[PDB]
Image 1 (tube, rainbow, N blue to C red):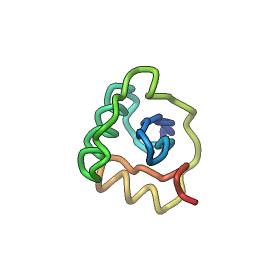
Image 2: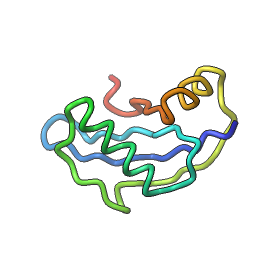
Image 3: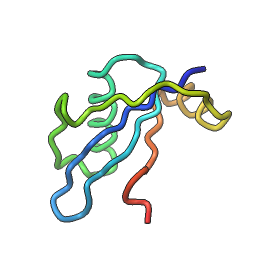
Image 4: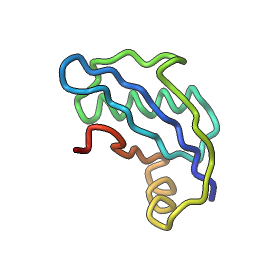
Length: 85
């Protein structure tokens, strides 16, 4: 399974620029935006504008067993790249 790494820029005001990558099997940039927005509304950080500039595609790479299950079950998996520590 090839994980599509969608580097997503979500600009929070004073919290922190939410720089996270979305692991998905879908090859749609719009879906990348959509999944991120659904996730933002889910966690509560919906207060950001995601455009074609905010959505970014890095590449597709080999996938560890962990993300295989995640994307297979949820459809997508967001990893907290920045804002972790």
